[PDB]
Image: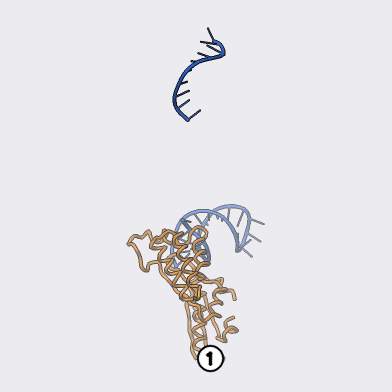
Chain colours: A orange, B blue
Amino acid sequence: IETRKIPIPPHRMSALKANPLVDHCKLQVRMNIKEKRVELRSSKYTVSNEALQMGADFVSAFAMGFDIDDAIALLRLDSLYIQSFDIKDVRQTLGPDALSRAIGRIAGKDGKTKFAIENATKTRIVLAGSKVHILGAFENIGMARESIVSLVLGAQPGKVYNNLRIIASRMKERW
RNA sequence: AGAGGAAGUAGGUCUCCGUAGGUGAACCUGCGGAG
């Protein structure tokens, strides 16, 4: 018997108030957004540490901000990973004009560039200021990470998109 | 002004918060902020 309790920030309170994991993978659940905690208890129906860690990874993904569609995709696919990249990681300058300028470069107007990168390398990323969150198979996450760090190092977005497209094709290929 | 003669050139997304207005619980818009 094992338990795991995860915190949520108060961003996602309503969507966590929206409703099932006990039916998904037989792991009993308690929640309280006043203490900001989610408790996952292992009853007798529970079998695997893999399933318990999977429920933990799912609830942490929904806390860190993905929607329920890609969240249950993370629940069902065992070959799907998440990664958290802070924007203060490896950095070209000591100037604190980083934040607005670089995340404007990454997003683009009406999310066009984030959307094009997502549809290109098949990942799903979310963006909240400092922290960016990438979701996908780990090699595609590597592709999106290299694209984003090139964007924050300051290459032109058209050039980055072109190079990303040809690398996306050559990795999609088998032989 | 005249018919001939001769010549040459051809780049802030998402969430949340505080606002002000809108049709009010909610919801939308705009702005200011934190992730």
Residue labelled with disc 1: A47
Question: Alpha-carbon neighbours of circle 1 within 10 Å: few (<14), some, or many (≥20)?
Answer: some
Q: Vertically, is A23 above or below A95?
A: below
Q: Vertically, is A44 above or below A159?
A: below
Amino acid under label 1? Val
Using the image as rendered, state which of residue A19 and residue A51 is in the foreground. A51
Who's the residue at 51% across and 82% down the image? A54
Q: Secondary structure at mark 1?
A: loop
Who's the residue at 47% across and 66% down the image? A166
Using the image as rendered, state which of residue A152 and residue A48 is in the foreground. A152
Who's the residue at 46% across and 59% down the image? A158
What is the total number of numbered labels drawn onto the structure image? 1
Q: Position of residue A149 (x, y in %)?
A: 40, 66
Using the image as rendered, state which of residue A48 and residue A1 is in the foreground. A48
Chain letter of mark 1 equals A
Q: Quadrant of residue B3?
A: top right
Q: Vertically, is A1 above or below A115?
A: below
Who's the residue at 34% across and 63% down the image? A92
Residue with the most extreme left position: A94
Q: Position of residue A25 (x, y in %)?
A: 57, 85
Q: Position of residue B13 (x, y in %)?
A: 52, 61
